[PDB]
Length: 338
Image (tube, one colour):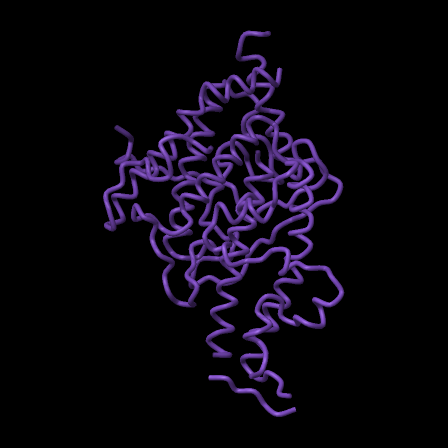
C-alpha cells in the first residue's frame, strides 16, 4: 500500500557522485573529511563520510542564488513531508548508485565484475548505505550530528524552531519526541522506495523490508563502521590487483627485487595505507576512549566479513621495525621475492 505508481522527482538531488560519477562519467569523487576542532556528539573531532557529503536534502534547502533555508515558514506537517520525500529520493538514488556498481562498497574484489547481490537480491552495499543515510537524517533533525555545514547548521536550527512553535510546550527534548513520533513514517519512506524497485529489478520480489522492518539499530560509530567497510573492501581490491600482478613469480636479479606491474600494484597499496592511517588513528582514538574496553578492530570485524582478514594493528602499525621489515604492510610477503 504505497504510491509506487506515482512518479516523483525533486530538484537539488541528482545522481550520486561521492565515490565518483556513474560510468561513463569519471572522477568527481568526495573524500573523508576529518576535522580537529569540532565536537561530534560528546568528543573531539570526527571523519565525515563521502556519502554524508552527498546526502539528498531535497526541498529542505533552496540552492538557488547562494543557498537558503526552504523551511523557514513551514508547518511541522510540511517539514515532515519534505523530509519524507528527501528520504524517499535518497533511497532511490542510493539504489542506482549501488545497482550500477559505482559505490565503493558495491564493488567486487575483481575489476569489471559485479559485486555479489545480498541474500535478498538487492545490490551489494545498498542496504548499508540506506541505513547510514537514515541515521544521517535522524541526527540532522535532532541537531545531534556534526556542525560542518553552516547551511545544515541552519537546518538543524530551523527544524528546532518549527517544532517549538508547532508542539505543546514542556526545546530539544521536544524535537527528540517529535522525531520518535514520525520515525516509523520516515522509515516507511525507505520501505516504499524499496517496494518501487520491483518496477525495475527482476532478481527477486521486494516487499520493502529487505533493509530491515525497522530503522537502525551513535552517529560517530555509524560513520566509523562505514569507513571500515569501505576500507576493508578497498583493501581486498588492492590484494586482488597485487595477486593478479605478482602471482608467476617474476623477480629481477638486483637476493632479488620485485619489479614492473607487481612493484606498482604493491606501491599503490603502500600509498593507500599511508593515506588511510590518519583517518584510522582519529576514529580509533575517538571510538576507544569513548567505548572503554571496546576495540575498534572488533567493531569492524564483527560487522563486515571483508574486515576479517585485516589485522588493523599490523596494517596501521607505527612501530620502528615495521617500516623497514614490511615495506608493503600485511601484503609484504606477496610483494617479496622467492
